[PDB]
Amino acid sequence: MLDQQTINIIKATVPVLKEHGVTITTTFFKNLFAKHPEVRPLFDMGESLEQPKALAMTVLAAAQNIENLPAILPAVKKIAVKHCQAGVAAAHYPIVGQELLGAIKEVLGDAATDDILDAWGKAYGVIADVFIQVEADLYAQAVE
Amino acid sequence: MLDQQTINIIKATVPVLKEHGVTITTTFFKNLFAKHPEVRPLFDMGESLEQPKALAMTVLAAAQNIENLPAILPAVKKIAVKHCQAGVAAAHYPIVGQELLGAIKEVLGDAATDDILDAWGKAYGVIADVFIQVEADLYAQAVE
Ligand code: HEM
Ligand code: HEM
């Protein structure tokens, strides 16, 4: 669980990140696909490489709700179904986290202190752990 | 969210409460029904007054998992269905919390420091909030 200052940072800064949403989203996907070619096949439907554009913004929405994560469970469950369909693994989450933080660092710029970036790293980890556990149980459910 | 000290108290003491499970369970239900006659109709099937004996022990099991509450979601969802079926309200949860804490105080006796009881109050609140939100979404889902 997160300490209070971590939560204060998330609550205080997420509106800034949301205001600059288009930059976060596009930087995130650019860096994800460029630096991690191994995940590109998961985003291949069917026709140029396709993107769930709300992915990063949905992390931010979860973070905004960091104190009432149960409230976002209906969204999580639906996304989790798509993840398990696509073959998302627990080991993917640190990769997504790394590139999200890179995008956050870009948007915040001079305002991107180590403590603030650390805070978002911790928040992402808590949010990812929710998806990871839900998806693990979904994977288990599929071979009942 | 809970602070680290609160969590550490929960982790350290929940095994003691589990060892004394039968006393917690029986004290809880005795006091619940005696002190809150208005909830008795919810435990009325049909033929003696009925008890989900695992109710308190399931709070303790959730507390054991306080750091990975997503792990208990498959159980929570199933219990939530039963709650919404029975007519459990958000306003009921503080009542159950009160009588659970009363039972904990009974079992711990000499060891029931104010800080330990406060920690269990906070932990219960977090756990109850999970059920409350899930059940609120279930209630809403029923009239879509
Ligand atoms: C960590 C938090 C994450 C969040 C909040 C998130 C959020 C989302 C959202 C909102 C969608 C679109 C769902 C829809 O409208 O159908 C999506 C789709 C997708 N995500 Fe995630 N995601 C996360 C992590 C990941 C990770 C680690 C991967 C690993 C590659 C991943 C891969 C995908 C893929 C492949 C799709 C497309 C599924 C499809 O095309 O049907 N996501 N995600
Ligand atoms: C975090 C708090 C709570 C937990 C962990 C919990 C847990 C449980 C469990 C394990 C059951 C048995 C489920 C089954 O095996 O079918 C149950 C049933 C029940 N609980 Fe809860 N409970 C909680 C709060 C409450 C509250 C606040 C009320 C308000 C009166 C309540 C009323 C009931 C009733 C009436 C049933 C019987 C359902 C049936 O007969 O189908 N519970 N609960």
Image (cartoon, coloured by chain):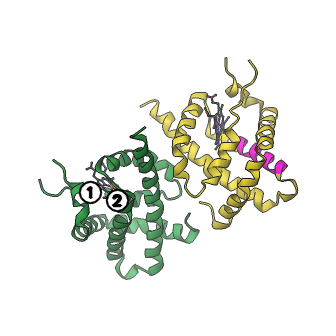
Chain colours: A green, B yellow
Q: Amino acid at mark 1?
A: Lys
Q: Main secondary structure of the magenta part?
A: helix
Q: Residue at x 48, y 61 (%)?
A: A126
Q: How dense is the environment of label 2, judged by Cα within 10 Å: few (below 14), some, or many (20 and up)?
A: some
Query: In x, y percent, where is residue B83?
Result: 59, 33
Magenta highlight range: B95-107
| Residue A122 numbered mark, or none | none
* Relative vertical location of residue B132 with respect to residue A93 in this rendering, above or below: above
Residue found farthest to the left: A47
> Are labels 2 and 1 assigned to the same chain?
yes
Query: In x, y percent, where is residue A113?
Result: 43, 80
In front of the other: B13 or B6:
B13
Judge: label 2 CB < 8 Å from ligand 1: yes
* Residue at numbered disc 2: A57
Q: Is residue A109 left or right of residue B87?
A: left
Q: Residue at x 37, y 71 (%)?
A: A101
Q: Residue at x 71, y 62 (%)?
A: B9
Q: Distance between the Cα atoms at labels 2 and 1?
A: 8 Å
Chain bearing tag 1 is: A
Circle 1 — which element? loop
Mark 2 and mark 1 in contact? Answer it, CB < 8 Å.
yes
Quadrant containing the C terminus of chain A in the rendered view: top left
Residue found farthest to the bottom: A110
| Residue A53 numbered mark, or none | 1
Query: In x, y percent, where is residue A35?
Result: 25, 71
Q: Is residue A25 left or right of residue A130?
A: left
